[PDB]
Image (cartoon, rainbow over all chains, first blue to last red; front, side):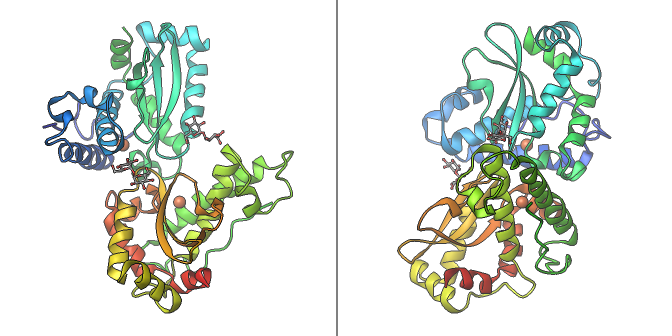
Length: 192
Length: 192
Ligand SMILES: OC[C@H]1O[C@H](O[C@H]2O[C@H](CO)[C@@H](O)[C@H](O)[C@H]2O)[C@H](O)[C@@H](O)[C@@H]1O
Ligand SMILES: OC[C@H]1O[C@H](O[C@H]2O[C@H](CO)[C@@H](O)[C@H](O)[C@H]2O)[C@H](O)[C@@H](O)[C@@H]1O
Ligand SMILES: [Fe+3]
Ligand SMILES: [Fe+3]
């Protein structure tokens, strides 16, 4: 069966941006529930012996909601880092300049998409088939991982459990936290 | 310009089921925000002079998300009361018996609809064209108000801000608070 990946850092490693408690519920409870829920759904079904990605790329309903959420979340914890934040670097920094003209322009473009992403959703930095960076929003469990020629680069969870303990209703404050945490390294690895 | 309706009871009136804080953020911030956003979008569009209900039955995208959320929320506040909870009464109680056989059947039915309502959503007790009761789920800002022949009776907000402060990730606990607060007098008024 599937297992809950270990967090890539200490539970308080992302303080003061994302709290030890948010990580305890978000990773320890929510992510974990998606994993039990998927395990509880695959016994004696096609998805029996398949990899997570194989499953998301081939299901609908409950199996997809749960599998995608497991993948989307693991992608999310990686998008954050106790040593991330600040100016982008290497190849990603450059492709962001190619696309938006500047990092600041990219930042404002992402924020806009994220604050306005209606309901439980996800906002992604992606690499397109033409090799260019773009920002796309997904709702609930939808993930670009299932889009041909689209390479997820980074993601921001916008379901309210991701920031309500720490920022209540103000997404902009949460996003301020994300930019302090952004894992550019994970970003460049995915990009290249 | 639309306005934030006043809360039907004191901010601590739903304690311990729904805290003073949830109400301050939920009613005082979340709901207020929809009001300001729709008030910001109507000017210069074919909605300027229409009623809230008129807007939500004819709008799209942003104007709809907003107007509907205002309607849904106003309905939601009325579905709770410091003097509600417990067994259904009068007309609604007997209709529940007619459809589900027993109040408990109805209840287990509804809880199951609500608990599995993926992402931001609403679970509704609606009165159908045939005169019977049914439970239906909408996601994000969708509302049965836009379905002809379908009269909305009660609703439970399932967006996470509605319960996270008080219950974190456990919707069933939230639902326990909802059944302690159900406003049967409002349900019966809408049914009659
Ligand atoms: O995994 C169970 C089902 O979850 C989804 O359906 C639920 O959530 C929807 C909103 O996201 C509701 O409208 C619906 O009423 C719920 O049952 C999923 O779409 C279903 O295919 C799953 O079977
Ligand atoms: O009012 C702004 C827009 O809100 C919705 O679209 C946003 O939220 C969607 C998810 O619910 C995202 O997919 C989308 O990218 C966001 O822009 C609404 O559907 C749009 O019509 C509104 O313009
Ligand atoms: Fe999440
Ligand atoms: Fe709400």
